[PDB]
Image (cartoon, rainbow over all chains, first blue to last red; front, side):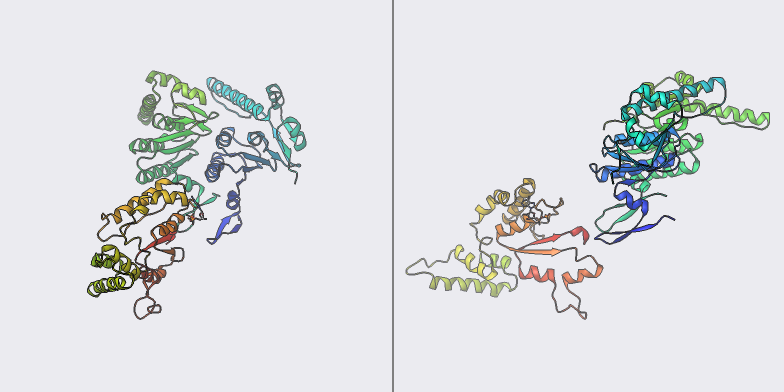
Amino acid sequence: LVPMVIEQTSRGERSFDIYSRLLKERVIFLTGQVEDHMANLIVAQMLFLEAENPEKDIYLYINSPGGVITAGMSIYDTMQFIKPDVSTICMGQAASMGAFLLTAGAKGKRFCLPNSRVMIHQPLGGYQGQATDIEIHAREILKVKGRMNELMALHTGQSLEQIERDTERDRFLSAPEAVEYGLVDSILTH
Amino acid sequence: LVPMVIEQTSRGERSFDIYSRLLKERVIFLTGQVEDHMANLIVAQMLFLEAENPEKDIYLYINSPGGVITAGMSIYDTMQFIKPDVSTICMGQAASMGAFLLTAGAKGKRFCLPNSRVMIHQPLGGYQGQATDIEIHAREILKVKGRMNELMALHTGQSLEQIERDTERDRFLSAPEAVEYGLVDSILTHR
Amino acid sequence: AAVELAVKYINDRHLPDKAIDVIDEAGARARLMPVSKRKKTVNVADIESVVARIARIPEKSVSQSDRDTLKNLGDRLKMLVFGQDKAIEALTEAIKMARAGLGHEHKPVGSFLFAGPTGVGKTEVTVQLSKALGIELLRFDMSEYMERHTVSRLIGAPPGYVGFDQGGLLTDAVIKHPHAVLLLDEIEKA
Ligand SMILES: Nc1ncnc2c1ncn2[C@@H]1O[C@H](COP(=O)(O)OP(=O)(O)O)[C@@H](O)[C@H]1O
């Protein structure tokens, strides 16, 4: 059961959840497989924070093992569209889509923990049916890979050739190695 | 769990969930597969906002992967019946039913994110039973397919033949391609 | 002018004896103030001075030579409280008509709702206005009057209950100072 923290306000005492109290401090948590409902929840929190204070930077933790690629884009596009700079603190496992959000953070504000593990791989999807139908879906997934590879290079800054090269096969990158690849700015000092 | 957000008021603080707080700002959320139950919640929000302010425009986010067409008509009919214009923003992806509701928004207020996708295809409804019953049900699904194509033509502006060709087989339309096809006026980058 | 001015500036006493006091008091001044062979006639100006003392006012409001202050009231307030000229000019227009014979038959001189942010001199414009017109300032904190039973303090408690002896903060203030500025801050919380 989620705890029920108490907040000291001049008007009176108010009861909030641990996640809800953290939302007041512009702290958003992300975990579990990416889902349409899960993504829309993160998007809703981002919109509320923007209206409250468009200047104060937002913090978004990531501890998800990856999920559907389509729903993840809704979080990415939302992060770019909103004015506040949403930092990305990768606290645990970060899969391809989980890593994509980490790269999507504002430049100079992304972070990662020293023992955090991030792995990026090409989008994995499958489809079956008639020969004509598989061809349409086959072309679409390739287009998605190009879009993910193109946007990844822009945020990270690495050449597109290197991004598409290593992403073909499953790759596991540690936190210190991430700084070399340009995935993250630097680890937390303290 | 849904987080709670507090809005300051003169008399006292009010606690509302993240979905209800955004609803107060005329922001509806259409997430997940379409269904008669979830659709009933969407139309309920639209009617409620109409009474609050029949002039302000409604904003319907679309991040659904597709669903039953029967429930979709309730949302589509409600949008056209209410005076306020509904702004449809495609978040993540829009399937056949989601795309139909996406283009169903008022002209000039339909938008899609630069990385969102828009898929459109004919209905996949199937029926089984005796040959006589199949003929009756088979004739009905064709009417729905033709009706959806006609409604899409009015909003998208393309001819019925063009919609039939594109809807004959599955097709994925990227965010920029959606503007070319005529589903939305432009990408949501500036306001 | 004695009966007219006395009724407006002296409400405690009744009109017949009130008019006799101001008329008789004017003659007394003509006995001591003149050094020798001065004007015997009692002009309207001599009545405005005696009636002013009875009402404890500075003689500016009752006097008919205060038009110079009202004519430049808008410019004077700008120097004291600069900014939001549209807010300052609005007050002068309502005050001018009230003193020009166009005021409401039974409503107050003016009712305004200073809807604005904090720190824009919303209360400063009121205190400075009183100094310009030379009238008492009344300030009431609506935050105190938040409970349902707090309204009794403003109008007093009914007979047979505690606080009946007290006439009431609001009623005793306006009665004590008929010509005064009334300020109610944080009315929304009331
Ligand atoms: N526009 C202004 N011009 C002059 N002083 C101002 C102005 N705005 C605020 N102040 C100062 O702010 C203080 C509080 O003013 P007050 O009218 O009580 O504020 P508020 O309307 O926010 O309650 C005073 O020192 C006042 O002189």
